[PDB]
Amino acid sequence: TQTMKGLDIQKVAGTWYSLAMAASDISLLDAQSAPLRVYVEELKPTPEGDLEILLQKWENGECAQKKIIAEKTKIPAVFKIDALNENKVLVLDTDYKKYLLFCMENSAEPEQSLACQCLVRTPEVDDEALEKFDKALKALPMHIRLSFNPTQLEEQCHI
Amino acid sequence: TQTMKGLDIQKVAGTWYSLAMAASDISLLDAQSAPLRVYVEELKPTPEGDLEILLQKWENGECAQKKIIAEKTKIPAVFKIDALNENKVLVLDTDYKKYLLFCMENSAEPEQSLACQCLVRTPEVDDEALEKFDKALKALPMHIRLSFNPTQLEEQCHI
Ligand SMILES: [Zn+2]
Ligand SMILES: [Zn+2]
Ligand SMILES: [Zn+2]
Ligand SMILES: [Zn+2]
Ligand SMILES: [Zn+2]
Ligand SMILES: [Zn+2]
Image 1 (tube, protein in one colour):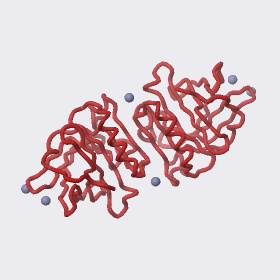
Image 2 (image 1 turned 180 degrees about the vertical axis):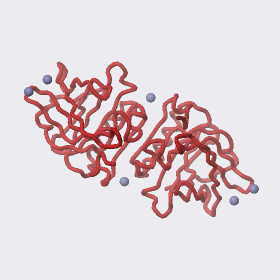
Image 3 (image 1 turned 180 degrees about the horizontal axis):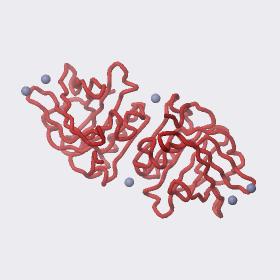
Image 4 (image 1 turned 45 degrees about the vertical axis):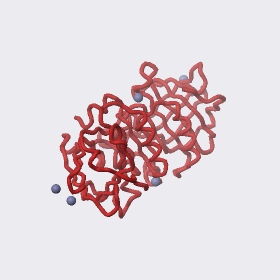
C-alpha cells in the first residue's frame, strides 16, 4: 500500500463528499449498518498537523455524526486513529481542489479491514477522480466497490 | 448489451454457485434484503427450451428458496421472466464446465434495473471466470460490484 508523497495536510481543509467506496471484505460496506459505511462531510486539519475527520454514519435507525481524530505519525500521509475497529488512515492522493483518495485499515489484519474512499469537494460525479480511484485500487485485493450516482451523492447518509 | 451466440441451454443444467454480482444501482444489491440480492443454486433447462432458475433469497429474516421460470423468446440467449421486478434474463457467456455469466433487467428501465452475475459450478474462486465477468462489465454502467471470498462462496445465502 503506497501513500502520497509531499502531502500538505492544511490544504485538504473544508467540505467533502464521499463519491466512491471499496473494501477487501463485503460485510464492511454491505448495507448502511455496515461498520465501515461512513460518509465524510468535512476534513479539519489542526495546527499540530493532525486530521479531524467529520463523518455521518448509520446507527439506531438514524444517521449520526462522528468525529475521528487522526494523529500524525513519523510516516508522512499516514495517521493513527482508534475508531471503527481501525488504527490507520492512509492518504493515497489528492489535488486539493477536486478529489482526495484515502484508506482505513487495521495493521493487525489489513486483508480483512481495508476500506478505501474517493472524496470530492462538490456533489457532482467526477470521472477523473474515479479513474484515479480505480487505478489506485488495482494493486489492492478489493471484494466490493461502490460508486454513487448524482442523486445518492447529494443524499450521502440518509434514511 | 450483447448476448451469447450459439447457446445450448441444455448444457447449463446442474448445480451452480453465485461468485460475483454487479448492478447499475447500489440499492439493488445493498444488503441481503436488497431486491436483486439472489444466489443461484441450480439451473434446470426444460425440453421446450425454457430455463428454470432455482435460487435462495433473504425474506422475513430467513433465506427462502425461489423458482423463476424463464420463457424462451425469438431472440436466442434472451429469456422472459416476471419476477424481482425484472422481465428479461440475458445469458452473456458460458463454457458450460466452469462458469456462466448472465444479467437480469427490466426493458422499460434498463439503467435502473440491470443486475449481472458470474456463476461457477464448484464453490471455488475461479480467477478466469472473474476476468471474463469484468471484461463483460466494461461496457455496462455499473455502480456496485461484489466478489465473494472462499468462505462467503460456500455460504451463499445464510443468516
Ligand atoms: Zn491543537
Ligand atoms: Zn495530536
Ligand atoms: Zn449511472
Ligand atoms: Zn415441459
Ligand atoms: Zn414455456
Ligand atoms: Zn480476498
